[PDB]
Length: 95
Length: 256
Image 1 (cartoon, rainbow over the protein chains, first blue to last red):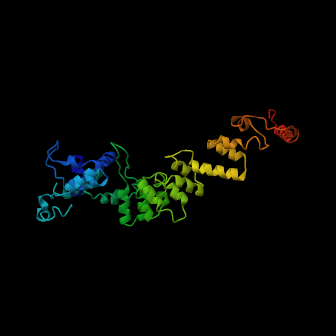
Image 2 (image 1 turned 180 degrees about the horizontal axis):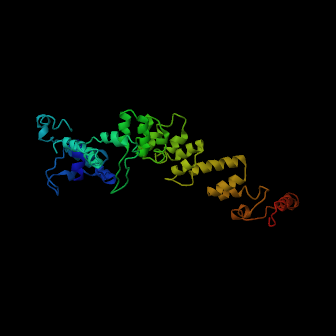
């Protein structure tokens, strides 16, 4: 709920809460938590979350996870109100 | 969920100011536009906006919305003060470095994160400010050099919070050993003895204490020095230590 709302809602409707120790350990280890069907409310879009989470996994080390997050950088699409433009801007808008 | 905030803004505007200001405050920050309530109520010197602290690991809020709103809408020095009034350890560093207010800079750089700690340290070297740089290198990584620079700027409370990390003798042993080298260079006795005692160098204070032909006290000739007897010669007994005895009689003391 944290990751989805905080980062995906950065453009959709802003609502952010963070834990800096948890977010620093995330900057070392966060990438694999963000699969959809693993104890999740479901119905969640993680476009911003995938992109920012991959960057955070890349940054602070755990050089395995930097490479893993390179493979999982961002490929996601804005919702159907943005469908006429994020058809082309799916990879473009968030790397 | 459709990347939109318009009905939240409309609800905030619907009964914004009818005694239902909490309604608009709710339906603006989620909507992203709480500026209008700053124009209405935080133009009325709502000095703070409920700055916070650790809840789970850390959380915070700020009067910085008020600040940057003022800074964009003209009241830039009001924003700078609001950095103190948002306790901005960053904007009281960075945007109070753009518009320099040291009531916001130093108040938000006395104890600020190393990232901004150095950012006011590197901001403050060229003004001839070793104090500022040392007062900004207390958690900024420069500590032993900051002992050396505090030795230039004669800072010891700033050096106290520098040596908060390392040896908390208000200093490093390099500074105290430099002082020892000076005091032995001067040949002065009492400050040398006291500082070497404070810097845990009683042996260096020993060679200057009892043969100095001065009045010698219980520590000054018994703690480090084995003998309270400064008299080692009978001629010295009858002339120099006799003068020491006459001085200590004139001191009002009866023991020495």
